[PDB]
Image (cartoon, rainbow, N blue to C red; front, side, top):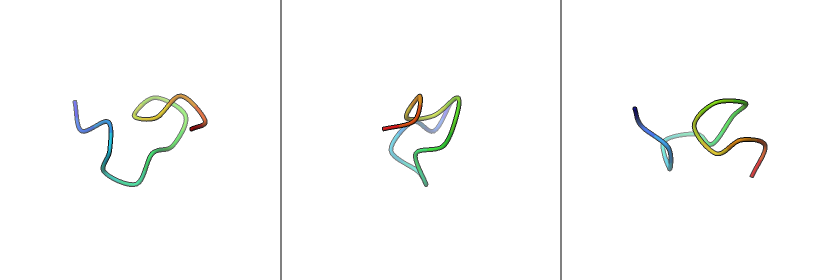
Amino acid sequence: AFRPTAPGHSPGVGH
């Protein structure tokens, strides 16, 4: 999973 890659609902968990 690409967390810091356009941090959305799953990647950044809203962060």
